[PDB]
Length: 133
Length: 133
Length: 16
Length: 14
Ligand SMILES: CO[C@@H]1O[C@H](CO)[C@H](O)[C@H](O[C@@H]2O[C@H](CO)[C@@H](O)[C@H](O)[C@H]2NC(C)=O)[C@H]1O
Image (cartoon, rainbow over all chains, first blue to last red; front, top):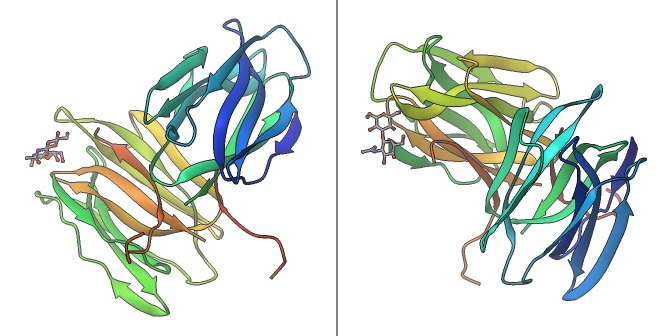
């Protein structure tokens, strides 16, 4: 896939992603906070199209992500993130995708996700999270 | 289980844990680094005996944990940490315990585990890790 | 702030 | 050192 890395910002305002119940997570774009103003992240797009887009709009700054989880599984020969769920202090967003495979999660007791990096080919191959106080 | 919380330090020099090949993780203790001196964390003891001790002595500072992984699952009807694996830039310690149930994993691309907290009854019930640059 | 220093903490894994 | 600020990064998952 194509590797991406947004780097680190002040916080997260919105998450735009897309998925397909036939397959996996496809695209990913984050609207960050950068010192109390919106910074529109790069839009990381699958090599293919067909996904259903979802906008998670968080009530920033009072709402923030406390856990990210998901499932990874084989889709037509690619091992990919098939499902994501974002749990905030306010509510749960997802699951988006297919909830089948090996689970993963990052729960956070103290600290903020302040960025994402990863790789997207046909689907979201994998991703990492910058964390900060 | 009884709660423990070592707090945060400069680094990790050694981990002393015990485990049982039919059950779960039992005792857990850390020798941290604090500003250059070994800081001998309290031994967090299982309420039961019969475990196998292991000493993971790291070549601190050049050697450090890059991933902590494991499995959580039922033992005697409690969800517990049934196994742990510590992977450093120099090698892999484990799995210790029983590799069954739901896997979990924290790989680190940047930063260090500088503390543990959690809870031990008959077995390690849960744990968290403090991260720092 | 208080005078107590703060650290990122991830977890817990295990019993909820 | 570099003039590039650092930050904790965890993962990847996938
Ligand atoms: C001492 O027997 C029991 O050992 C188990 C597994 O190690 C566990 O720690 C028990 O503690 C209870 O654990 C539950 C989590 O599975 C938790 O919900 C309870 O609040 C804990 N209760 C007490 C009194 O520790 C432990 O009792």
